[PDB]
Amino acid sequence: TQPSDWAYIAGAHIVFSYQGQSKTYATRALRVRKESLAAAAANDVSGQWRRNILPKLVPRQLLTTSREVTLEEGWYKELLAMVRRGVLLEDLTSNVDDDGAITVAIEIKPKWGFLPCAGHLQPPESVSIKSHVSRFRLHQHFRGRADDPPYDPLDLFSGDKMRMRTALDGLWTMWEISRGKSNNWKVFIGSKEISPDDLQRGLLPMGGDDLVTNITQLTLSALQTSSALPLLKNLQQNLDPIDISSLAALFQAEHPNSPIFDPDLIAEVSAVELNSFVDIYISDPQAGQRMDSWSLRERIIAYALSAIFKDCSLFVRGVLKHAWRLVSGGESVKVIDLDLKPVKNIQKWAETDEKVWKHWLKTKGTR
Image 1 (cartoon, rainbow, N blue to C red):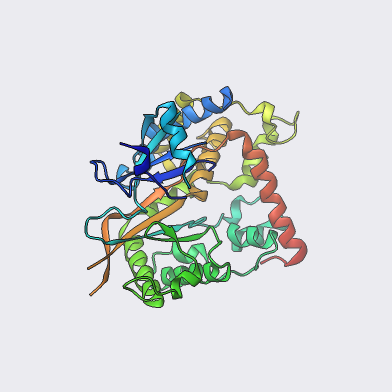
Image 2 (cartoon, helix red, strand yellow):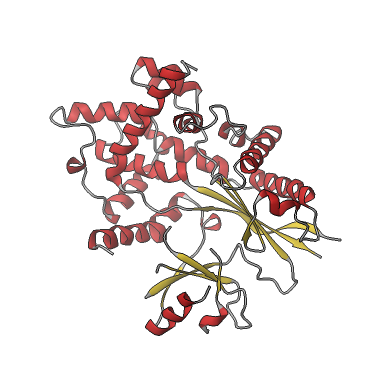
């Protein structure tokens, strides 16, 4: 339990791995930061959300456990020299096996697993675009990136083996072109975040390109077996049942008074309010489609929840062991980055949404 034994392993926090330790509790990691009351408050409800509410929507098997811990003052200062209270995580990316087995991990940002129905899209000018062009393609185009990326989220969420394979290859392609700086695809080997030139550097029992093939196949197999992708799509869809454009329309009927999604008009969400809605949601997830179901406040809450599952990540872990082979360990797929998003940000989200389809119309067209 000494500070020397923790190894620096890459939001604005720092993570450490117990990857140089002969003690018990070898297979866990530690994250430490280096605070406003309103910030602590929100992070407290997010915790309540993470512990009590979120397991209702996503099965516990696909969730990562965390335990809050108190570290002495001196203890912390020693740990940050080398080149408060923190949290103990599962060490899924580091080398933790007696075997000398090499840990192989992949992080994917799957994006939206669906397209909004034409029947719900508000401005008629935008209907054909949002009904046929994914948010990913729209957002990519807006930032001046390639307007037709090789990765298509609908391929990954399709359930078709050849389609899912094409999506994974597309993720590899963008990773290579971005020289490993793309956030959509991250590969971890020996806890080190790999870049394309690290691949052709021969430091492993497995060659560069042979590693890529097994990683793709390993991930492909893991994603097909897990219910993570079909489950994610339904949460993305149900919590945003009639698109942001119509939800914005509903808001205007209620408050012709004010600008749309005015922050002063949107109250902060309590754990009690949040948990209350999730229970009604579980009772009938597809209720959001009808107009005699969820309230406006509930829809704003639902949409904020939708944003989490839309922007979350998928984690696939494998092991290079022993001839050398790539093998899956336990439940290789996990759904991570599931913290709460501030509900007042819906105004920003609506503005981002209108802006991306408008930019597409202005420069590329209607499809």
